[PDB]
Amino acid sequence: AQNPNCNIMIFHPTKEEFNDFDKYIAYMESQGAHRAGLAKIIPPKEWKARETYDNISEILIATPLQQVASGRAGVFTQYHKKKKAMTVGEYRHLANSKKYQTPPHQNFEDLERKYWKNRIYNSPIYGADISGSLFDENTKQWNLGHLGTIQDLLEKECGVVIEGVNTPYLYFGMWKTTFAWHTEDMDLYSINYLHLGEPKTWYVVPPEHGQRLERLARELFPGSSRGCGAFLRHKVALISPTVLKENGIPFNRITQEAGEFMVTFPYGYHAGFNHGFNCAEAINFATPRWIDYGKMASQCSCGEARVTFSMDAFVRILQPERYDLWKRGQD
Ligand SMILES: O=C(O)CNC(=O)C(=O)O
Ligand SMILES: [Mg+2]
Ligand code: NI
Ligand SMILES: [Zn+2]
Image (tube, rainbow, N blue to C red; front, side, top):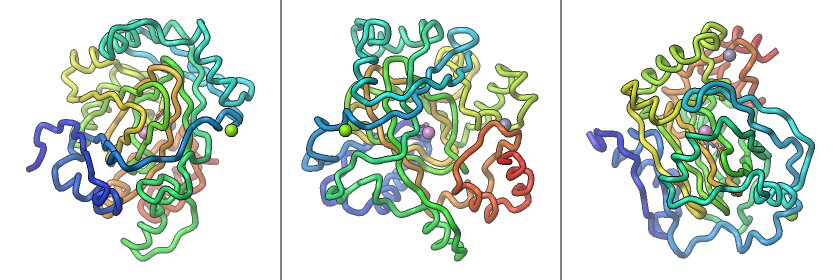
């Protein structure tokens, strides 16, 4: 078995290898990359996402989210308070202000220490989940707006044609902005490109160990667990690396820098934080190997998780027994 310790693997495809997206994902899996739940892909030196980032300031963040924490430094939840709209140029100036800017630090490990010590005492503002793309239309390789759709993959594997669409989302971050522990909708893959700015640190649990994280989460968030049998779908819970280590949970960590892609694999729990002002693009995708994960994915039916239009068909076709309860949670 390749990669039996489930380490995060880093790949350096050539420009030739960067042509065929599906083929390269399958290659990475042939080397065991998926066992980690996360991989890094450094694009060939010849590649670029677009020519410059000098003209993005007028993008609107219609609903910036203030991420307010509750709990203790290493075990907390966050809720998202909606703020007034602002442009990317206004958000960048806010990120760089004394109130929100990255503190002085020695290296990434020092900054990580400071994040986990102090995150809960601040409420950073995240421009998350903005439909759109920063890839140039002329970028033909790894253009996250031009991937094969999940509806086409389901149709190709299973023969059933379904409604729905699959488009990318932009994320504008600042110091301490946080993504809570989660797997993707329907345990899909994700791919994330860091277009510009400061790094993003990731934590990940191997898919074969995801139920160990779920059992810890139920212990640490006992009211939430009584409320919902899949409360991590709410995307609000944080657990620090120190607490994971104290509880024996297998995990790994890595820092993504501007110009790098990350892929999350089906049922790979992940969480993390931004180092300072940045912009990422991400989208879900599927392969043949996902279908079995989609069929087994947990679902939230309590009403909290509320998701896209296109998840309906996935539940309806892959999980017909669960469909009526899930759809009630949607309505
Ligand atoms: O960058 C973020 O805030 C969150 N991104 C993801 O969870 C992802 O790409 O799967
Ligand atoms: Mg603009
Ligand atoms: Ni994700
Ligand atoms: Zn729920």
